[PDB]
Structures are given as C-alpha cells and as structure tokens.
Image 1 (spheres, one colour):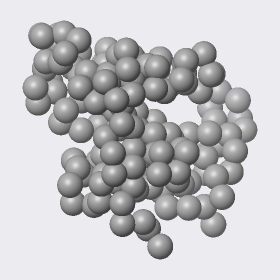
Image 2 (image 1 turned 180 degrees about the vertical axis):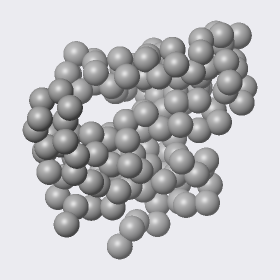
Image 3 (image 1 turned 90 degrees about the horizontal axis):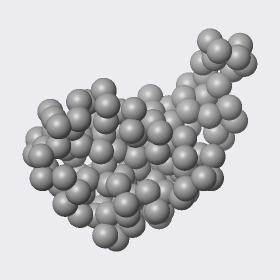
Image 4 (image 1 turned 90 degrees about the vertical axis):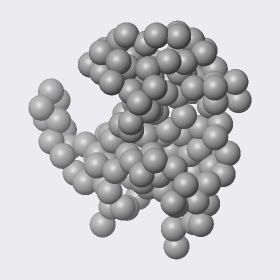
Length: 147
C-alpha cells in the first residue's frame, strides 16, 4: 500500500484526498502506485543568505531570505507542473549552481556521495518523477530523476 515515503492526506482547500511523499516533498491528486545502486538526477538550486556559500554564477552575493528562496522554488514547480516551462529550461536559466550549464544534470550517483536529504529524495523518486522542495545546506532544490 503506497511506495516508500508516500502517504494519504486531506486537502484543506478542496476536501479531496491527495498523496504526499515526506521523503521527496512531492504532492499530487493521483495515487502513485530492489532500490537501484545508482540513480541519475537533474536539479534546480535556489540559494539564500543562510546557504553554506551564498554565491553563484548568477549573483556574487545572494541576499534573498530562505523564505524568498522557497517562494521562488514554489513558483518554478508551478511553471513546470503547468507545462508553461520545462525543468531543463528553468534549471539552465535560474539554478544557482554551475550544473545549470548542463540543464541541471548531475549525472549518476550512488548512496553515500551526495548531501543526505538530496540523496534520500533522489532514491525515493521513480524514473521520470520530480520532487517538491528539497532542503540542504547548499540551498533549496527541485530534483528530477532521469534514470
């Protein structure tokens, strides 16, 4: 009953049941449905003033608050989910990581290499699926599992 991390919840707005993943922060109306050694993922990182290194190729001094970074992240998720913009396009333009130059692709990795909240979300995604906001010391990410 429900894959790893998935649980059922009541929408306050609509009164309909939804499904949420406490490991990936994914949420959706639809019922979701041998852990691989490696996964491949892309990400979009929004840094803020409390990030470990508040600097990127986009902006030498990042000054936004963590609250403002999360609003940005939420906005990007809305644009991706609506199909107004695709993930790769937003990562290329707006990610505060040099991975932006490869459409956010980080390549393949196993457990024990990445920041643990990043890793955990990555391995709880099925191929094709996207996370909600994932919080690490680097900042807030959206993760897309591509393999």
